[PDB]
Image (spheres, coloured by chain):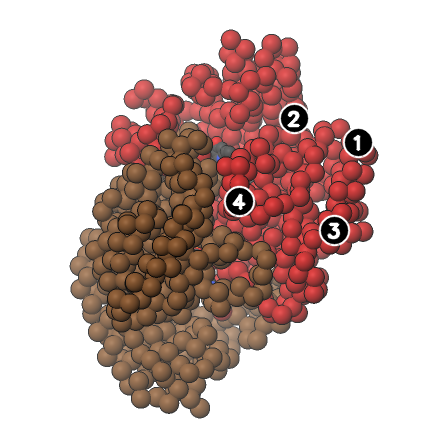
Chain colours: A brown, B red
Amino acid sequence: LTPEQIIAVDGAHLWHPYSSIGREAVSPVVAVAAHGAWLTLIRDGQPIEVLDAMSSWWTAIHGHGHPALDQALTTQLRVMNHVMFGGLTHEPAARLAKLLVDITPAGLDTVFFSDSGSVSVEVAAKMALQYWRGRGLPGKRRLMTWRGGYHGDTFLAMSICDPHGGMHSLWTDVLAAQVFAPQVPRDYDPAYSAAFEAQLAQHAGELAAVVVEPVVQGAGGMRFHDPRYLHDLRDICRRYEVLLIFDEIATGFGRTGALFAADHAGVSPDIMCVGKALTGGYLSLAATLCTADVAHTISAGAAGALMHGPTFMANPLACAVSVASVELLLGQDWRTRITELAAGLTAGLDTARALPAVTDVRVCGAIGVIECDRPVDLAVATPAALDRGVWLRPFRNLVYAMPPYICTPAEITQITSAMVEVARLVGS
Amino acid sequence: LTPEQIIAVDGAHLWHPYSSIGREAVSPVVAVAAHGAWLTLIRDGQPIEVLDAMSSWWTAIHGHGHPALDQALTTQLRVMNHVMFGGLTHEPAARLAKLLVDITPAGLDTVFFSDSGSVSVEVAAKMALQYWRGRGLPGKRRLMTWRGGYHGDTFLAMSICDPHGGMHSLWTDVLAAQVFAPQVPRDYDPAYSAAFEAQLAQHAGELAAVVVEPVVQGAGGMRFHDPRYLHDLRDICRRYEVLLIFDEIATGFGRTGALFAADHAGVSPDIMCVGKALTGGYLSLAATLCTADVAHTISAGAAGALMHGPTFMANPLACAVSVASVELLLGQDWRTRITELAAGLTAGLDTARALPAVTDVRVCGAIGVIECDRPVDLAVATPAALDRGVWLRPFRNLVYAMPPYICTPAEITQITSAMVEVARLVGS
Ligand SMILES: O=c1cc(-c2ccccc2F)[nH]c2cc3c(cc12)OCO3
Ligand SMILES: O=c1cc(-c2ccccc2F)[nH]c2cc3c(cc12)OCO3
Ligand SMILES: *Cc1c(COP(=O)(O)O)cnc(C)c1O
Ligand SMILES: *Cc1c(COP(=O)(O)O)cnc(C)c1O
């Protein structure tokens, strides 16, 4: 198929993320290649290389078509594509489970693979719910979170999504009613933790778990908070016998300046979700990890087993490429690499503070955010970043990036400058 | 890692489908290779070749390591592993969307890609809910199904699974309260459809949709029903304005002797789910298709969009291999092939009707079932099937098979023979 034919089939037959059929404001751009930090896209009918400032929705940490990850995939392909995980095990699942157990915060000893972040969240909740049924406390079934969060699109995951971010108004009467604390602030305020605890305390007899994105809230608005809030949640959850779940689907694998964002605070959740960057952007795969205590309680309970099992659980191809992606990350000085990226993002985005439409500029590891005072019009900003050789996708009032780790100082410069310019055109 | 090392790691760190940690009665077998219809498994230190009678949980329709599917994957690997589907489109997605629209029941014109069956089911339910919100009937929010069904493990998916099979209590005050018709009989009885209509009639104003597995109920108990009920379901849904959803995640791509099980009845659902065999069992991928009318109403609704967007939506690698998998199926005389497999399963399984422990023997397309009078002990069944060079995995009281389509007559006969012998051992 040609790019013109792709557009036509696409417009008649393809849904896209949170999109329409036949009523699309803009119109998707055809991608034809991706290599390293660059995509090849079709503009005015011509191929152009542009920087993947978004890491293809936070996935491409090592860049596209990284030779070590292509080979990991090809090697596995020639030997064993997939076998069912029911009754069978295999080397890629074992290898990856060992890495994950070793590199995640202390005490996360068991791994349940699934096919996506949303599913890993539902698995996490199911772990929490079965845990308490195992302990003889079935009333502990509600979830608690703070506002501003995002956890995925499946119905249970939607229930702990920010009520505005996740559009709860469209869903009156259909979602579980969960317990929401106020928005977690940027700077550390012990009074917020105290208020969080008081709210939790009166619900504890009915809460299975607190579920949060640690340090960085992504799709709910790219807000950062002081790691010390996570230390306080760990302490609150411990004292009131409520499980603590960290969703590190966006934050995991170095993105925020630490291996896992949990690490900034030096704290272990009881249950953890990872995804997005796990396969270095090659294939869909996710994992939920839980402590030995959670694992044994579930296993010694009435049901005798965790009641879940995706068809493609522990797929050998995804697992093989993830092992390579993780080892590649661990085999380099990733901490310096992120520090440099962060400096690059700070330096390049500094001039945007002055802009008339800009309310905030903030950076956390390989994450750079320009917050505006109004919705960023994509029909303006998209062609504007393409013109400068950058793939950028603003969302709501934010002009932001999660650049691949392999980006050079010159590439970051190029990214930040495109971002600064999108912010300027918003003010005019 | 060695086989022994894998077991050691697996027993300590890996969850399996519907399994425990530390309380596993049987212990998983190590798989080291898969080619065509054969797995290489490690039995007592030694490698053996066994027929994949289960098709790796109903996925490997073309066998493993098929050269056309291998190629399609490596070809796409060197070009473009993945890009975000937000704002972008690509050839693998448009080719596959085009195919899916062309070969599925008529009127199914739009395609939403996602990573797994359970997710595609939650997407289907979301389309139904938003459709009726588009029409000003937000009261239409419940789902109706008949008993014995299975739809996945995520929380909405769970709510329409059989209330005994899915252990709905266990899940007391957590699942949405859905409407359940009695188990659909094998043989056609018009009294059943009349009772279904009468039950639907009294919930019509609160029903978004009817959701069923057409013709074959999979994980709920390998039950077959007369395609004519689907015709009745279509008629009832039309007259009462309740959307019809077919979960074809197990049944699709020729498995029941028709391309899609809906074809046995000539019926078009409003919304359809596929997965499992979609990629020929290489990678995880599912799809939810809906009619133009459904797409336009959601798009014209208050929301202006379908509020869903998985990270790895429409992953190029996964789509490219699906394209090649669908093309490979459509390019051969698949109907004759499936008729041949069915005839071979029928002939090979006949002798089991006489066995003292067998209550039924049924076949439908490339699905063969020995229904036993007691639950089947895997600790006896699994080694027995291995001894005969077959990978069989019984479920509850079923010794069943869904072999790859590339299985020769002799391989089918080896499969059925191992099934008979397992059924014989159950009777003692
Ligand atoms: O043995 C399995 C049983 C189930 C299952 C259990 C209870 C209810 C429904 C199910 F599909 N689900 C399964 C799902 C699997 C699998 C095995 C199983 O390997 C590939 O993915
Ligand atoms: O643009 C996207 C927006 C959302 C989204 C929308 C509303 C609320 C939360 C979200 F993550 N989710 C998305 C998920 C995507 C994606 C794009 C988007 O490309 C690959 O996966
Ligand atoms: C993206 C995301 C999810 C959902 O991931 P999918 O693979 O899109 O289902 C869940 N949690 C967090 C924090 C995320 O950023
Ligand atoms: C296997 C199956 C599902 C769920 O598939 P996953 O990929 O395991 O989420 C849903 N519906 C039916 C009918 C199935 O057979």
Which one is in front in this view, the residue at disc 1 or the one at disc 4? 4
- Amino acid carrying label 3: it is Ala
**Sequence-wise, which precedes: disc 1 or disc 3?**
1
Element assignment for label 4:
loop
**Dot 2 and dot 1 residues touching (CB under 8 Å):** no
Q: Position of residue B310 (x, y in %)?
A: 48, 57
Which residue is under mark 3?
B204
The disc numbered 3 marks a residue on which chain? B
**Dot 4 and dot 3 residues touching (CB under 8 Å):** no
Which residue is under mark 4?
B173
Element assignment for label 1:
loop
Which residue is under mark 2?
B363
Q: Position of residue B324 (x, y in %)?
A: 53, 48
**Sequence-wise, which precedes: disc 4 or disc 2?**
4
What residue is at 29 percent from the left and 22 percent from the top? B45
Q: Which mark is residue B189?
A: 1
Is residue A55 visible in this depiction of the protein? no
Which one is in front in this view, the residue at disc 1 or the one at disc 3? 3
Q: Are marks 4 and 2 on the same chain?
A: yes
User: From mark 4 to mark 3, how far is it between C-alphas?
Assistant: 24 Å
Asked whether mark 2 and ligand 4 are closer than 8 Å, the reply comes as no
- Please rate how many residues cluster around mark 2, counting C-alpha atoms within 10 Å: few if below 14, some from 14 to 19, many from 20: many
- Amino acid carrying label 4: it is Asp
**Dot 4 and dot 2 residues touching (CB under 8 Å):** no
Task: Decide: is B236 above or below B421.
Answer: below
- Amino acid carrying label 2: it is Val
